[PDB]
Each structure stands twice: as C-alpha cells, then as structure tokens.
Image (cartoon, rainbow over all chains, first blue to last red):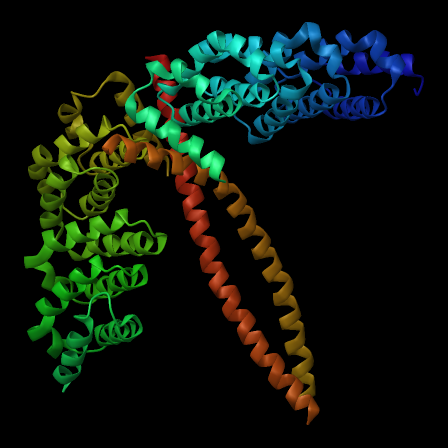
Amino acid sequence: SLDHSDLVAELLKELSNHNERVEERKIALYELMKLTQEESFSVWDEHFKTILLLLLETLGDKEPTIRALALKVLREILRHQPARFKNYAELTVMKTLEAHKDPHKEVVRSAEEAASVLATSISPEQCIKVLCPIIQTADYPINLAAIKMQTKVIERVSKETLNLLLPEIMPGLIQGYDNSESSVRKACVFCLVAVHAVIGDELKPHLSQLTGSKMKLLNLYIKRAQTG
Amino acid sequence: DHSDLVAELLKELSNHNERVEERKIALYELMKLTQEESFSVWDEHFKTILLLLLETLGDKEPTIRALALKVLREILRHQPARFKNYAELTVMKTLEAHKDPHKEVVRSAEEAASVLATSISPEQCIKVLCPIIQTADYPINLAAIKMQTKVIERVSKETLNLLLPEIMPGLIQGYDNSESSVRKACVFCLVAVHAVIGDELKPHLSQLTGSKMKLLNLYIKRAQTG
Amino acid sequence: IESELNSLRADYDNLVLDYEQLRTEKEEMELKLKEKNDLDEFEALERKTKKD
Amino acid sequence: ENIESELNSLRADYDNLVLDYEQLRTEKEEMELKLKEKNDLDEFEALERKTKKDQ
C-alpha cells in the first residue's frame, strides 16, 4: 500500500524473507530507497532502528545482488539521516568494512561508496575512535578501508582536536607503515600527509619510530602534495 | 654492393646523441636490410652492427633507444644462429633496458627479450639466466625469470634434469623475494618445470614452506585443468 | 559508381559507430588503469628510497 | 562528375578511419594485457594471503 505506516510493515515483512524471494525484496529495497529521498518525517522518527538492523542483516545475504543493493540503500540513509547513526557508529562502520572483503566487485564497489559517505555522516571525532581499534587490529583489506576512512575524517577535526587524538591515531598509522601490504603502507603515508597538512611540523616527534627511508619517502609525498 | 650502403649506416649510427632524425633514417634502413635476403651483409658485418646497436642502447634519446631495440629484435629473429658468441652480452643489455624510465623503451625491450627466449640456444640461455636471476635486482631478476620460463619449455626432460641443480637455487631464492611479481614469476616457472618432469621435482622443493608448497600445488592444479 | 557510392557510405557510417564502441572500451580500461598508476608509482618510490 | 569527387573523398576518409581503428585496436589490446597481468597478480597476492591464514 501507499500509507506510510502500512508500507513500512509490508517492507519489513517482505525484506524479512532472507535468502529467498530475490525480486520481491529488490522491489522493496528500491521502494525503501525512495522513502529515504523523500525526507519523510513520519517513517524515520519511529522506524530507523528497525529498518537499519534489518538492512544490516541483509548485507549478509547469500545473493550478491541483494547485498550490493542494501549497500546502496544504506548509503542513502547515511547521507539523508546522518544524525540517526549516533548510537550505531561501531555497528555501521564494522558491517560496512566487512562488506569490503566480498568476492564480487559489485558488492565491494557499493560498499566503498557507502564507506565514503560514512566519513562525513558519522560524527568525525566519534568516527576516529571507532576506526582506531579497527586499524590497529584488522586484517587486509579491512585495515586498508579503515585507514582510507580515517584520512577522510581527520580532515574534519580542528588542529586542537586532532592533536588530542594523535596519541590514539598514531599507533595504528606507524603499525600500518610496517605492514606487509604496500596498499596499506601508502594509505598510511597519505593519512600522515593529511595529519601533517593540519598540524605542520608538530607531527615530527610522533614519527620518531620511523626509519630513515620511510621518513624520506614520507617527506617526498608531503612535498608532492604541496606542489601539486 | 650492399657494403657501400652499410658504410653509410655505420658512419651515421656512430654519431651518438647527435643527428637524431638522420640516425632514425639510418636505423630504419638497417631494419629493411634485415627483412631482405642480404645474407652477404651479415657474414662480414654482423659483429660491427650488433656492437653499434648495443652501444646505441645507452643513447640520451629515448626514441633512439626504443628504436634500436626494435631493430635488434629483428636481427634476433632473422639471424638467430649468429648470437652464439654474444648471448650473455645481448641478454644483459636487453635486461638493462627493462628499467628505462620511458614506457616506449621498456615496452620495446620486453618484446626483444621475448624473441631472445626462442633465438638464443635454450641450453645456453638457461645457463646465462641462472646467475642473473640469483644476483640481479628488480626488475631485471623479474625479467630474467620470465625469460627462463619460456626457455625451459624448449629443452627435453632429460636435459632439464641436468640443469635442475643450477636452475632451482634462483627459483627457490626468488620465491622469498620481497616483490610479489617476482614470487609469482617463480611459481609460474616452477609450474613449467613441474609440467615437464612431473613428480621428480619433489626433492628440489623440500626447502619450501608449507604455505608456499600449498600455493604452488594450487597453481599446479590450475595449470592442469586447462 | 553511384550505386557503389551508396554502399561505401554505409560501410563508413557503420565503421564510425563501431569505432565509438572501441573508444569507449579503451577509455574505460584507462580509467581502471589509472587506479594502478598511483599505487605502482608508490611501490617504485619505495624501492628507490631503499636503494639510497 | 561531382559524384566521382564525393566517392573519391569518402574512400580516402574511410581508409584514414580504417588506419585509425587498426591503430586503436592495437592500443586497446595492450591495456587488456596490462589489466590481465595486474588482475592475475592481485589474485596471486590474494591466494598468498589465504595460504598464510590456513598455515
């Protein structure tokens, strides 16, 4: 039906058919996406948590097209209702980061887009504190995805705030610079470029644990970022 | 009289770093002689042309270097039996071109090293590539490993066994290389060695870890399904 | 010749459309290749600093 | 006579388009080989990670 309250019940009823009824659930997800674009006041005031939790379980569906679609819907709820994810930051981050290791390109691509909007929708100081333990303990490619997100989020905190968070940010960044994967090391270099861009030379004491060749490589990308 | 024209080619192509367009014509002229039945030229002037074409690989002009590699590729596949006494020199110079900053030179150098795998004697090529593989840095060690994979396919199973004590050290060593492309090139070389000698390869792989043995058997299985 | 002209124009018009399909395919691979370039440039800069 | 000139110009332009397409077809095939090598390499790096986890 078209009645907002009746429609949500039907959407929650249809999308509860996990692993079955693929086309009926795709229609419900496309319908759910339209409600997100409408800025519907009545739908989101009462059913955000219910929709989010059902949408997050959908990311674990056996169907790759169902997963990739829920990641596009999640991207819409993230940038249309960003203030509602306050109490679900860790859950939304860690579920979106797990989608980054799906075997299907269409699923990871849609998750990389959701993780891009997630950097500006989750509170920036709150987003850093979720990403730090993930960065320091996760395996490839989730640690790579979390570092890329932290780079986007570090650009949004003031210089006074970023210095206070450096004792917690720098451990994962120095650790990822020693990572076996070159893509992780570059994301750390580019993250340190963002940290240097904010606090300038004040970052220098934090890099004491860097080798000379990594310090030289890092200074190279700071200069390259400033030259253009 | 082919020789009088060659004298003009040898005179022009000795002008390194100068007369760029005139040497491009001269190098293109040398390439036409390669396609022709000009075997009278090569009986007397091969060494002179090879050394002048190899010295040209150190030219400041990237288009002159990339062109000399194009002419050399033709002399390799039109006069392959003549490189017996110049294998190591031609291999080591062609491998050095693989680290040129300009794509046009490395791309043209990858092609010369491709013809070189089938033009140089395969038994001689393996014995040249082994010390290079074991001691060279990226990407020359990577380039030399790819070449040996193409060359190993051309020796008999009886001949390959004699070269295994000399082939396997660089292959096990390159499996521990920091570069993933070098580790992958070694697996594909071991897949080519396994494809020839079968289960006889097992004692040589004793120094491999379980995870590398598993990865290698994984690519051995993948090679058989084709 | 007039009949020959009409047939040749069709082949030229058909090749233009076919050429567009190849240009769009090649330009997409460039977009995909561009992702690799910034990463492989980093790896090459690492080797150069380690050599020094 | 003007029909002859129209054919004459179109035939030349068609040969130029043929040459441009042939040059582009060889250019596109290089990008395929480069993409395929990178893809098989990233698969190798991914297969390497799985063997380390299981060992």
